[PDB]
Image 1 (tube, rainbow over the protein chains, first blue to last red):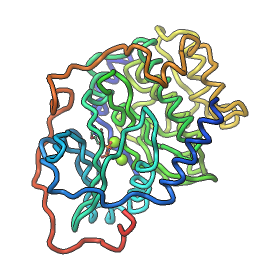
Image 2: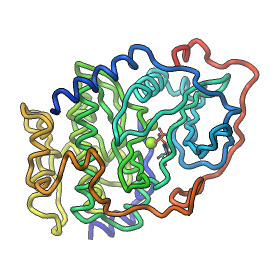
Image 3: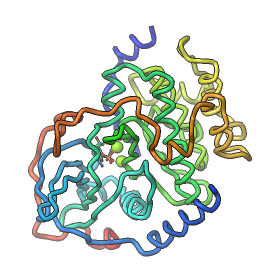
Length: 19
Length: 337
Ligand SMILES: [Mg+2]
Ligand SMILES: [Mg+2]
């Protein structure tokens, strides 16, 4: 499921702003 | 009426925009307690104001780090705008000041935690729950854009839940008062509008895009475009394709096709009707816009509070020494702060 894919991904934590 | 409210709103804002408040406290008037969150140039800490006994959230920005990263203008923007705005769903700036090493922005402390923490723990919000939050963002964007402000960093991490279960928007770090188009590549990879990524000029429509991503993420539990590397996210954003979870209602999906619209001429919030396209959408049929503004709607959840100065809704972070140099660092660059 895409939820399972998200949870396994490296971007489930707090995301830094970029600039 | 809305028109008359915005007119009085603009005048209050403009007076403070033209004459910003400065140096309205100092560091030794606060006991520093605990880090609540982190970002690029430093820390947000729980603090206690010794004289009043109030708790606040103090944002600490290292002047040298701001300069090395070329964020001077963004930081001056951040402080000038936040001290000038006034709206129920915007965090209140209380004091600001600077010393030799740091810039300080002392805000009302929003104890409920980030929407991010609650959203990840619970998985996803029900549609009525997401709508409640989204409605506050819609009104807030109406307010900000009427002032010629572009917000540019909407994400669950920058959204705090207050004691009434209502949204407080924090982090004006990328906010900017701009009447034309603008070009700075900034924001959060997942939330970036195509036109930002494609190095086109852009305008306030990027915020309406960011609203679509937010609603999607609240309602699905994952964002519409994710991948392990930023570059891979951007390819997905640009491609003009989004898949919806089967549990999304037809109205939600329809709202989202219009918000996550690549063509600026077709994006909701950017058409002749403006914000009304969104407010009058079917997904928001049950929304009492006035009642939301007056905070009379009952929240989908009130956060747990074990009393004053309680940080149970925030993650723990490694504490660090707050060091103030005996030499003034970057005095000229931060004169107007
Ligand atoms: Mg932030
Ligand atoms: Mg920021």
